[PDB]
Image 1 (tube, rainbow, N blue to C red):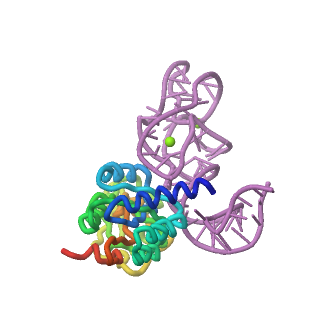
Image 2: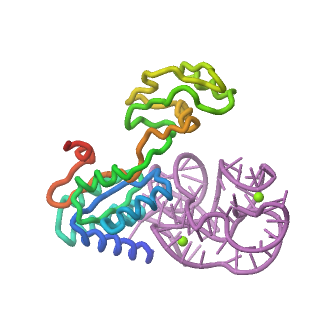
Image 3: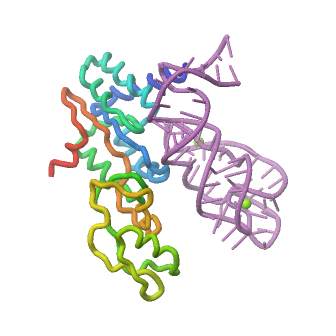
Length: 205
RNA sequence: GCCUAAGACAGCGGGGAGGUUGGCUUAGAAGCAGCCAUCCUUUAAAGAGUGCGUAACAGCUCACCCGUCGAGGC
Ligand SMILES: [Mg+2]
Ligand SMILES: [Mg+2]
């Protein structure tokens, strides 16, 4: 299909245009927060997104052109949704750059935790009612005090590792707690002769 | 004969945006009483909106795009 070629053409051509080739994940990012992130990184980095299949060869075809073996090897890391990123910036300040400008998002169900998850206590400030019942339902001591539910507790709710009930999840979406950081997260990257898994980036104090 | 392994049909997940509450009208008309208009931008993709819904908003969803799957579709 004619449009598919023209894409791959622009994909590759944008790939060798810069020294640092980055594979990032935008999955579960909201369109406004995206476009905000977008214009802070505008002049630095360039991005396009396509079917990950078009991108599975993509770079591999251009691994042929520049003649490198292991740049193709990064295509062996592709998951979820994917997009390509190109810049003159090596990863390490680039990673900070992505993780700093991220935003808090509410939590959804059937998901592990990035961090440990807790509550802001006492007055939740609405009318009393049904809302207190499911609060109890998972592990939450709560009473009523002037005008609505108080929560006395400070201790763990869910400790990381073990997952969260289809909703154990939100009293928090209802409480307005958005404990987790989302934005562009990195699948993997590297340029010259060496390749890393994203674990390495959190580290180096 | 056309599309389809460069990922079809269907289903499941995620997105479904900003200008903006388009303009006028109207007690009010925010995509969705009715008239006219029916463009730009940020884009992988998103109509000045396909069907519920509100008192009007909010909310649910659908065209469109991405993933998941993996052989048939007009
Ligand atoms: Mg209406
Ligand atoms: Mg547009």
